[PDB]
Length: 222
Length: 138
Length: 78
Image 1 (cartoon, rainbow over the protein chains, first blue to last red):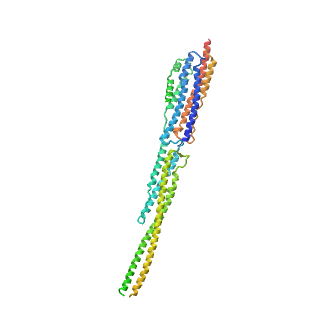
Image 2: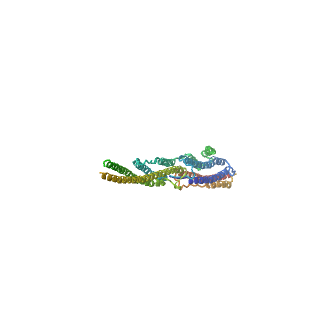
Image 3: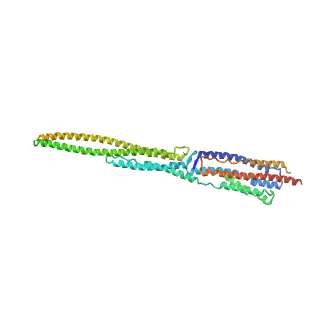
């Protein structure tokens, strides 16, 4: 269990670059589909059904894929927010290894025993010659108080690391992609019949999937 | 003869008491020297253990590897480590100061034991002179 | 009238532009092993799976649209 915020922020930049490239290619695919609806090279009721199919599904499908990229980017930023809030670590290059913290913790017992044993021994030799010369044994709690506080930091950090490692995101992107898959599968089932088929035409003219994609995009704009 | 011998005999009796008192005080001082030698031996052993088992072991919980521990959590941890290491060094210095005080006390007691032996030798020689004068006076 | 050449050229540009959408590059974590950050590749893979499914349908829908145009040419000629 290890995390390097340097690598995480580098992946955030690489993710933004790939999202920028995909959004440009998606916009090109949107323009190509738009050119079909504005074309007069085909006419009739079959063109009315194709225009309804493109404007109510094909273009919204490309729009929702851009919304999926924006949602994936927002979830990556929120995952960084969740890490920097659960562990309390706002450093941009922070490196934390749970096994390395445990290795530092495995040496505390030997130091704690040495401090407690030597303190008992020195206190004995100081009290044995107290009638000859009274000498003060130094306070061992001056060492063990920050020693335990330092151990708490290693105790709390390792715990929050293991705690954050089990944190789960929401189903926002999973629900968006399931809506994409179900819509595409329905368009596949209608591809064997004609565009002017009663069941297929009624589906192409239904704008509920378009309104759903419009609502996801409008929420993203605020 | 009777007031002259009693005069020197009384002075010999006092020097005899001074000898026995000086020897007893020297025996008590020598007993304090022995107890401090024991304390110096055991304190030096615990000082060496404080260096190897406490001060020298601090580097094993430091975490100076930047490739495995870096950020604000290391900063908060390095602060408490510095306070722990500074306290362990201070407590060792305290033991070294007490060890010096014990050594200086041993030296002062050895000087006092020699003075008590010199006082006993003087009292014994005075007793022998007074005893000879008291014996010849009769 | 129906111009099949212009229509087939536009549907060809649709199939080209949709297939021109590349895979979302997977993130690379060499030292980072956190599950919340490692599990992002499953979301990227499921994204490219849904996109590849749209690309397969688009390749079929382009052929479907071209057939509707030539059916319009054949039936309007009669």
